[PDB]
Image: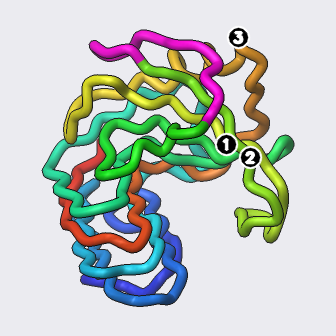
Amino acid sequence: QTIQPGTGYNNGYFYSYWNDGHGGVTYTNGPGGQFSVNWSNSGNFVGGKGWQPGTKNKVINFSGSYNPNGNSYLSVYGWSRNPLIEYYIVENFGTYNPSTGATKLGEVTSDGSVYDIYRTQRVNQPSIIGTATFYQYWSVRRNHRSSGSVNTANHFNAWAQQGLTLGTMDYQIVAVEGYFSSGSASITVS
């Protein structure tokens, strides 16, 4: 059930699989909300299941295993149009804290941990509307985990209070992203 890069629907859930074409990634869709990624000396990829379009008060449940060997994240990942924003709610990462070198814009408590909030910018990088310059919003969990519940309303409200405004919501998935690393992960979304 391993597939090419692309999006669509599998077992009622929206999925989005993408990579830079380097190779070494194997993304598979499972039953219901299950999806599995296995990669060894890969390029950069983003894959996972969720909802298209996402909403601003959804409660997202994820469970399974996540074992990275290198640079990788596990997060609630999505975009917003107008303004163009790429947002992460990082639950667990590998060898690199994605917020390293980013300015901290506050904290929020949700689902049993404290999240630190950051903003970064991507200049002329690819996006859901083509090459653009856009901001990234990060909610990085302190107590890492590979299963549990995410109340996005807590993060989206905390972001709004600090001056980080989301526009119209695009896709919103539980994604495994990995940049030139190895690992395996099997996540079930609900």
Q: Tell me which secondary structure the magenta stretch mostly adopts.
A: strand
- Of residues 13 and 175, which is closer to you in this image? 175
What amino acid type should be assigned to the residue bearing mark 1? Answer: Gln
Magenta segment: does it hold 43?
no
Where is mark 3, residue-wise?
Answer: 161
Indicate whether residue 106 is drawn in magenta.
yes
Q: Is residue 181 above or below residue 174?
A: below
Q: Tell me the residue that label 1 is attached to.
A: 136
Q: Position of residue 49 (x, y in %)?
A: 39, 57
Given contact means CB atoms under 8 Å apart, are the residues at marks 2 and 1 in contact?
yes
State the residue lying farthest toward the front: 101
**Quick check: 115 left or right of 54?**
left
Magenta segment: 102-114
Q: At label 3, which amino acid type do we have?
A: Gln
Name which quarter of the figure residue 54 lies in: top right
**Label drawn at residue 121:** 2
